[PDB]
Image (cartoon, rainbow over all chains, first blue to last red; front, side, top):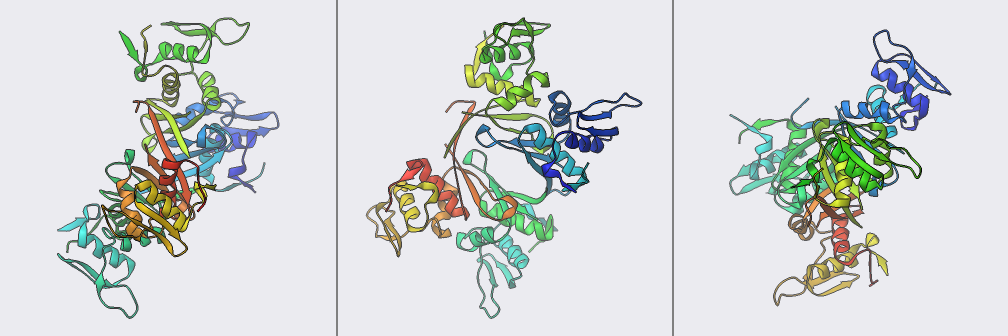
Length: 117
Length: 115
Length: 115
Length: 117
């Protein structure tokens, strides 16, 4: 198995697609591909690296924060998840905001590990 | 009839903390809360919501994960720990009040019988 | 007469960012902001406050230290870095708007001439 | 010189006393002593370890936060310090809340270093 915190690239993209409920996700060395629509066509999907793909997900999902000490180095992502006094979040880090965010998304669905591709 | 834990203050708050902490014969006179914190102990004052000496060690010992105060002024918010992170959260005019209310909520929930 | 940077939006916000970034002949038609981002370049659309492709890299490249959204809903607050820690802070309905307003404030201050 | 982040014990107490404007602060191996009042008597002062001494300082000074990941390990302290869009804080860590707080206080006054006692 692979630790979700270490996920990167096509594999990370694949787990996000799967979490998002996309069709026939694949993770070639060339990159992840999926169908994001009713009866759509297979198209590249790189939310962990393409801002166009990842950005909307960040805005849409209940992300509560991103932090980077001194504006450099690693990012930490916080994704929100019902009692009055309670709170639960999912928390992952990564070298870029998109990587941190997508790892958090994957962890919120599959937990700490995911089968290796 | 019942009391909201978030509104707890003074001796009553100290009492619920004693109880949550497993102290013996807690009580809550207007004079203040008293309990026995030891196997063979005498009843002694216990004011974790106002006495730093009593409340401080509890803050350090229990899994409190944070305290926050906007701009360093006004109300405190307390966060008590339980890739997932789940917490109990309560506020108060001081750090000790926020902390103890959070402790009491983590054990009894939102309300407690009135004293 | 002048415009508050915190209220900046759309093409105007994109324009101030282009300017702060040192782009050439920035302009702000209703159609949108355009500029030259290269030594020998052509005028091309530039919408960092709405286009992720344009705004995203700026967020990653500039010393942004945080983005926050209460409960993962509503307005974003952006924090841009400058034992001491000093920051520029601005809000907006989306992460890109918050980020760019913060960028523009860090360079021009609170107001800017109206376009 | 000594890094403020490494300050501990009587020495840390001494720098706090000094920052606070106490009289004849001292830092014996026995512990820090000072006069905190107009013409007062020299008395023990241990804000980095005694809650009775440190607690009130935390409440009085503009501390904005204390953080401890998962409720265990090291504490981080944030002390507030005037443009509309700007913000400055002092930030130090320590094994306990009082140590983190007092190091932050000392840093807010003397910076990163302080002469060794």
